[PDB]
Image (cartoon, coloured by chain):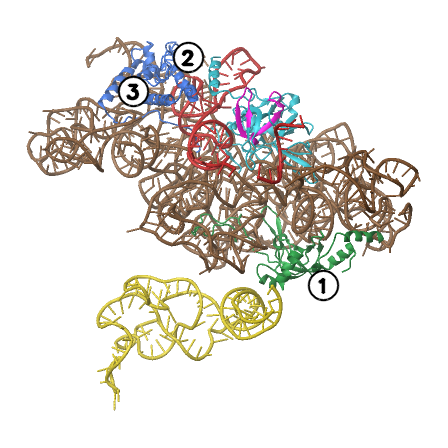
Chain colours: A blue, B cyan, C green, D red, E brown, F yellow
Amino acid sequence: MRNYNNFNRVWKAPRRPFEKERLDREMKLCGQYGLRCKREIWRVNMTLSKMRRTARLLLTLPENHPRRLLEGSAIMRRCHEYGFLDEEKDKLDYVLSLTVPDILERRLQTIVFKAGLAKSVHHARVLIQQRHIAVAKQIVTIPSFIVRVSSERHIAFADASPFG
Amino acid sequence: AKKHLKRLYAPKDWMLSKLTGVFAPRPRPGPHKLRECLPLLVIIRNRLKYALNAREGEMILRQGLVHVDNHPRRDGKYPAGFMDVVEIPKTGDRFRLMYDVKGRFALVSLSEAEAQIKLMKVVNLYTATGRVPVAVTHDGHRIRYPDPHTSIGDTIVYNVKEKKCVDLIKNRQGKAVIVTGGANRGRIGEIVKVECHPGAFNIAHLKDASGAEFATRAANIFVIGKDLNHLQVTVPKQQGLRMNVIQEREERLIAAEA
Amino acid sequence: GIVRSRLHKRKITGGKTKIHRKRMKAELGRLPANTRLGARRVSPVRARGGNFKIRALRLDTGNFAWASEAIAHRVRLLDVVYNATSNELVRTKTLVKNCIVAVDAAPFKRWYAKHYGIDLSPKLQREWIRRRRNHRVEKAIADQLREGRVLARITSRPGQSGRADGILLEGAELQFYLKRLE
RNA sequence: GGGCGUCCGUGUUUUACUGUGACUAAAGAAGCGUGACUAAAGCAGUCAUUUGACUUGAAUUAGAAAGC
RNA sequence: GAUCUGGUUGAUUCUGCCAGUAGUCAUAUGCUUGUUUCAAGGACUUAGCCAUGCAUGCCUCAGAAUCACUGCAUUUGCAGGAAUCUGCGCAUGGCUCAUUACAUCAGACGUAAUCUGCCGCAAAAAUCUUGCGGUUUCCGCAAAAUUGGAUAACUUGGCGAAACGCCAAGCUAAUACAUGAACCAACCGGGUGUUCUCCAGUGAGACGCCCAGCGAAUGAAUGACAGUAAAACCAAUGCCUUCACUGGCAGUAACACCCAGCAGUGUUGACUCAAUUCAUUCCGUGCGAAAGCCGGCUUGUUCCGGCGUCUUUUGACGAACAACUGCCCUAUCAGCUGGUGAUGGCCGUGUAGUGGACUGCCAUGGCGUUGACGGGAGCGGGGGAUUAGGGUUCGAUUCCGGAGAGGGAGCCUGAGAAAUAGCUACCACUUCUACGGAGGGCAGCAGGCGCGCAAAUUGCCCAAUGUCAAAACAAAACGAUGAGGCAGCGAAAAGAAAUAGAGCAUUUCAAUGGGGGAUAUUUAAACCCAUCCAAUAUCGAGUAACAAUUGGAGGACAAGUCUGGUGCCAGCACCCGCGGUAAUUCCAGCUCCAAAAGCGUAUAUUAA
RNA sequence: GAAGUCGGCAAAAUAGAUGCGUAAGUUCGCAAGAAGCAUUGGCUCUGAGGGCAAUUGCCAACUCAGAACUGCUUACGGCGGGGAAUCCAACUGUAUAAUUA
């Protein structure tokens, strides 16, 4: 009692447990991004849904409405950071079209593999827990670390690792 | 007759984490009301940081090192609300407790000479035994033989050093006013006009600098100076002004670059 | 004990209030103190902030005011003549506010002579001459003063204050009670 | 000589609805900022370069009905 | 993601329900578990019953020290101080949801209808005391007011089985209690002398006398004004003019000196209020400069400083009342209320105060199909689940508000109680006893029984957050605090993420933390996390035996026309339907499927 | 305290008046005085209830309610015990003068 510490859900299980169309789409992502579980998919479905949904609400709204400017620019900024979107795209309509890969491409696991420090994505996911990759001078052990686009220059390897 | 006051039920302005305690220090009756006041303990401990604990609260206070209103105060539960003057002679810092814009307590620093000055709103005016008139200030002072002109709603500029009332300030038409209470706190402006409403609140229209309009109940108005260009107290660094919420944000990004 | 709350009453609509609360000390009735003529008695009660209110069991002298003359005098209560609530309170003589009383009347005579010189120092004779003018006294009073008993109406609330104080009745109401009395 | 301010004396319109505005506890919900390694959180912290700096931050919104 | 699918027919198209699946800080239960971070946890059934332990007390430079107490001791004693009186608090916090539908609660108003300790700002000239001498127990001289008797601890005797059970007698303190202070010391008034000082009777002046303080009582006055501009006659009175009350309206706040302006004007929307004046009161049921304390001192017959307290007053923290709008289901509850208050009136009484709250009299009202009355389930809300939207549902539970301490009732003390770790009684239970008696109240925290589908340690600590308090800390000398915090137990929920990576035979190049451990870090202490395998110098994984499970494989619904066994048997199956000798469904083996340190099942609920 | 006895036969019991209250059944009329509870004296007062004559004056005859004080040895006569059911006749009435109502 009397302990106020807020906790929350990050993910949701889909209705219709097994559809061979979805399950197919699931596995095709699990093997491609080297994912441990479906759980890590359903997560970027909800962070994408929440994000998407406030894009609708603000979008249904009249232009120059004070929420649409302030609260609208902030969703439209944070997607330029993290590089969910390209800095060429600012309509706020673009937020309303995003896909599960966009947020998975940005996950430190794929990027360490894309940056080329690893064989595919399984080396990359182990090589993160093995504590060797550091983002900028900061060792980061979480595969799901979402890599801010300003930070994609700095990864390299740890200085406590074998590699430094 | 309650004694304890819980964090979640403490006023938000004391600005005390929900975690890290069940309770907040409950202020005793005093000059200023419970819901609007900042205890001394929250001043030294949380605001000024001179004390990392409540244990260091009594270390510093019970020694009477920390003055408000020229008088040394021993009590961490003492309410010090607004217009108050909190001096520490040891370090040599001097604070007026005035509201910040954004509706928060800000501690203005002030010169040696201006801590003498304290100016207090006239909450009531009555006759004491033997025809003595008295004025009961927002602060809680009972001030005998005020100016024959003073009336409810006027400020009494009060010298806290030598104890006496220097010049007063009426309230009519344009006179600079700091809003105290009710969502416009700290926001300054002239009175543009006052609505009458006998038997109920008088709603009181104001105009900040650079033009803008807002209302309050006239019991949230505290007079200061004849014009908005002349004020008899030192207001916080953002004077009375509210920035647009979209200008506040994009100036925290530009400065964020360092 | 005795209680002043409403929790025992039929609602406007006639139903019972169901009491979920116990009695409070902020609801109290202190049995009546039924005052009477007699040698002074008092039982002090301490009430609701530490304040005492003086119950007067059995008080007699009492302090009576003669309005239109702006005076008062300390005068025995002779009798309880009339009461508007119960007729028993007269037989029993309980003194309660706005009872009617017969009062000794004698120091009023001495005052009215000492003041206007009229019996019902040449510097002070002419003052009498000056006080006469503009001034007149209703027969109905002065006719009562001859007897040495004046109908009064006791103004203090004798259970709370512990004293019986009143006014001498006047013609507008003095004629109402005299008739209503006999 | 005319004109505002104040007070008093003598000789007719509301309400729903709508716009704006006051007035309203925190936690909770929505939300800004912020690499607590990420996240659920939190309201913190960040920076020089030391013997402090940022006038350091802790924005803002909704919250039936009724009442103004 | 504003989504639907299997079952009625030989087929068809419908209605239409059952079944399916997705949540739930929704609880239970089953099998299963390596690591971490933050969490609920005797509410649901009994507001059942409780063994034992703890759960509030507090003293500074500053209220009372011969402990026949401990230290030091060439000073009359100073340094601690055990108990004990005194002052404050125990009315808060904690727990719990039995009661409860114009009650409680929410938002919004009100107290001008009131009580208010502590806390802030302020107020303060009521008072014939004391000593010496005398003496009529009364004058007269004098002025730093040098007041009183009693109680506890304690000693002596002790009673009693015992007991938060008691009795005598003897000592002694106060900021306990009781008394009490004149001149210093002002201004302002009312009433009046068979008072004398004057000048002509609305005369003035002195002096004498009784009374003139805050607060309370009754009475009287004040608590403004506003709808008109000249004149003159009389008495007084002012002022001018004369010489004379002589002639006469120029002048202009008031007022018969000692004060030539020391109030001609309190506050509200509004008051019988604030305050002022006059008349009688106040007998304890109000009023000290605590006749109080320790510090300075450059110094003591007005040096100075900070505390303590009385009475008055008004802000503040509160208390208690009232109630504008709104709150579930029921008519197989339609009339409800007035004997003995029901709705209103009058004079009271009682209250802190308003009031049918209550006594006496008077009237006949008040409420109801826009659901009264009755009954059923319920603490109210902030809020939670789920929702495209609209909604449906939950809210015992952290914050606010209400109520209770086994059941009922009564009350003392106090500023505040109808208080229960306070008293008194009865009821139901129960614990000691030497038989005479004396006790108890866990819906405080641990824990026990019981009950039940259902819920942890008789653990450490005040380090933090608050509270009370005579209180800073330290210095011989660290207040209590089961409030609160910390850990134990803890797959209720929630976040992160291991169980291999690299170039089917193999083979070998690294890497890692589970775990071990640490100069340590952490913490009140210990934990956990983080940091670490040399920094001169310290561990380690290959069948990774350091080995992932729980439910399924006819359909809905993703995944076998495998192989055994059984023969309408045993069993599966939410629904449809399988099994009666080649079973896609049971029991098994292999194989694949979904989810995965998590996964089935039951009931409740939301979407469907 | 019905054990008596064929059987509560006989006796006891109930009891006036006023207020509150009153079940099943029913032909709605009753049942009903159902059942049951409570009050009662004496004394000293108070209120209400009218007539007549010209607001005022004078007068008769009683009843009811309320209060204070005080008392009970429960104390003339007179005056219902009540409730749950079965059988029969609907009811009031008549009827074996002198064994049957």
Q: Which kind of residue does numbered mark 1 sit on?
A: Glu
User: Under tag 2, what secondary structure?
Assistant: loop
Q: Position of residue E8 (x, y in %)?
A: 14, 36
Badge 1 sits on which subunit? C
* Residue behind mark 1: C147
- The correct choice, above or below, for E344 with respect to E300 in the image is below
- Residue A61 visible in the snapshot: yes
Mark 1 to mark 2: distance in Å?
116 Å
Q: How many marks?
A: 3
From the top left corner, tell me how far across and down residue E62 is, in percent: 66, 36
Graded by Cα atoms within 10 Å as few (under 14), some (14 to 19) or many (20 or more), the crowding at tag 3 reads few
Please, what is the three-letter code of the amino acid marked with disc 3?
Arg
Q: Secondary structure at mark 3?
A: loop
Q: Is residue A129 above or below residue F48?
A: above
- The span from disc 1 to disc 3 (Cα, nearest Å) is 117 Å
- Please provide percent x and percent y for residue E590: 17, 23
Q: Nearer the viewer, mark 1 or mark 3?
A: 1
Which residue lies under the disc numbered 3?
A36
User: Which amino acid lies under the numbered mark 2 shown in the image of this protein?
Assistant: Lys
- Mark 2 and mark 1 in contact (Cβ < 8 Å)? no
Tell me the mark number nearer the camera, choosing from 1 and 2: 1
Would you name the residue on which mark 2 appears? Answer: A137
Give a yes or no on whether discs 1 and 3 share a subunit.
Answer: no
Which residue is at the front of the view, E575 or E193?
A: E193
In this picture, is C91 found above or below B203? below
Look at the image and give the residue range highlighted in magenta: B205-234
Q: Using residue B3 as the reference point, say whether residue F16 is left or right of it.
A: left
> Which label is found at residue A97?
none
Foreground residue among C165 and E222:
E222
Q: Mark 1: give few (<14), some (14-19) or many (20+) Cα within 10 Å.
A: few
